[PDB]
Image 1 (spheres, rainbow over the protein chains, first blue to last red):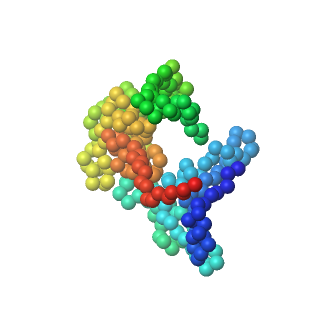
Image 2 (image 1 turned 135 degrees about the horizontal axis):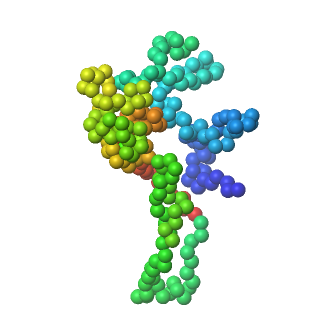
Image 3 (image 1 turned 60 degrees about the horizontal axis):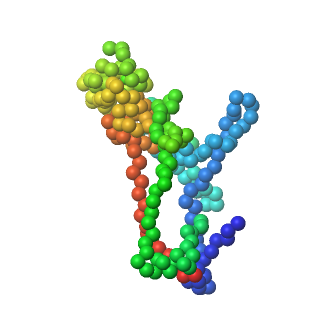
Amino acid sequence: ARLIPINYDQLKKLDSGKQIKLETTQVSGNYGTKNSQGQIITEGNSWSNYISQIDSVSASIILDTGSQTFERRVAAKEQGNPEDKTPEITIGEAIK
Amino acid sequence: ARLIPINYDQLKKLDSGKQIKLETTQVSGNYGTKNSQGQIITEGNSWS
Amino acid sequence: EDLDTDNDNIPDAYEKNGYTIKDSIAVKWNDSFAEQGYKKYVSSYLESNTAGDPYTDYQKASGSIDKAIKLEARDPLVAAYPVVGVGMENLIISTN
Ligand SMILES: [Ca+2]
Ligand SMILES: [Ca+2]
């Protein structure tokens, strides 16, 4: 119900070469699971509960074809941990 | 969202030696317990 | 040898002396496997959460917690604890 205001100084800046840029700081959203019945639920299934975790155990790989972009996370073993049983793969295997 | 107003007579009083005093009439708050798991809960545990 | 007063899946004897976690099981510490990357843990046999954080001694030691938690806090003596601050970078005044 409340519009986004700017002040007079900012308006004067816009009345020039100056342009507003948009940056996305975060995105909330849900994933789907099946409940005890056959129904798919996406209500309490918050993606932000996994973002930190996935980023901590993964390597980032991004493919840029010029027009499209594809971003991936591939799990990798923790270096010092003897109890980490994540299989080791090469960069080529991970890309494939 | 709503500021605390005073009227003109009160404002005139403040424009003198007169000072506002604060008194605390009560305090609400929670205590902690452990649930069936190991978690500490302080949500329905009202001190009052 | 088999007694868990605090019911945290680590025997009292193991908590008093050293222990480590192998295949999700607490085992009595031996120096022989210090050089394979295992760490010696100690904790209170009367407290399930020695550091007072939301995770038990077993959960921390075994790493069966949020993977974004730093490995320091896998030690039962070191608390899993976020220290969050706010910094101001600039302030904008709109004279109405
Ligand atoms: Ca124990
Ligand atoms: Ca304990």
